[PDB]
Length: 36
Image 1 (cartoon, rainbow, N blue to C red):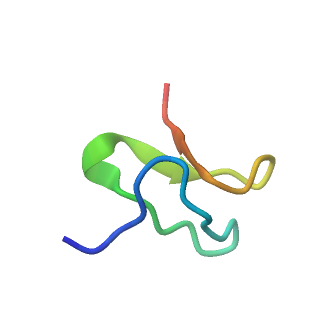
Image 2: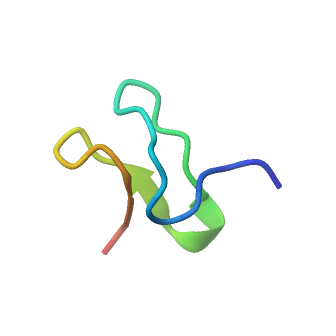
């Protein structure tokens, strides 16, 4: 269990968020945003 939950500061070039919670790092907001 090693990732970045929602509302965490992540990197766009290296998106590293929690996939389990359907998260992703966007180069627009630069943060783990819920993948709709």
